[PDB]
Length: 240
Ligand SMILES: [Ca+2]
Image (cartoon, rainbow, N blue to C red):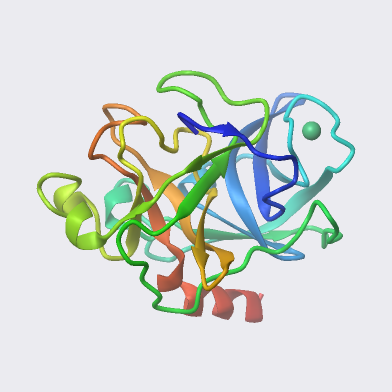
């Protein structure tokens, strides 16, 4: 997260850290959202490679023991059937991970609230992006969970020539673009929490930013619109 601030520890309890094994050590690569005690929602491009993955819930500081963490392996990876790794702009950047064991829900670990199917947010709706991703373009990961206020930019405006143009689809959500705050590498797969009817719901899965950089004016961070995949998500969890 570029231009963010440290989140209160465990204030976004559904946020998870997706890590892969590199030799005898582990490295954070993406964010994700705990949607069931044994299911995590993340981006398809995060699990495109054949690596050994593990999920960490209740995490805050990646390098220190916070006394709230739970580590669990990944038993199954279900990528959306239309996902095309060579065309992130085509959409479908979403994947569901079945955890090897069910995590224990508590003060630091809770399920994320998903939107009702088809829900579209009005322009400039209040949302927050969270993650341990780079704090600057071509920079380094954040040690502690970061958050940044990132209001939405409706489709009509985001898909115009002044912003992303035809690179964005109606199956995506755009947020930010103020040139100061944005998601960045490492935030991928993470949530976009938006205030709807008094509660924060996960409306987006961080997908991509401009090749020019993370925080670019009129180049909002783009997210997979969760509300367009509710039926798919329910069908996978109900038959797997
Ligand atoms: Ca920690």
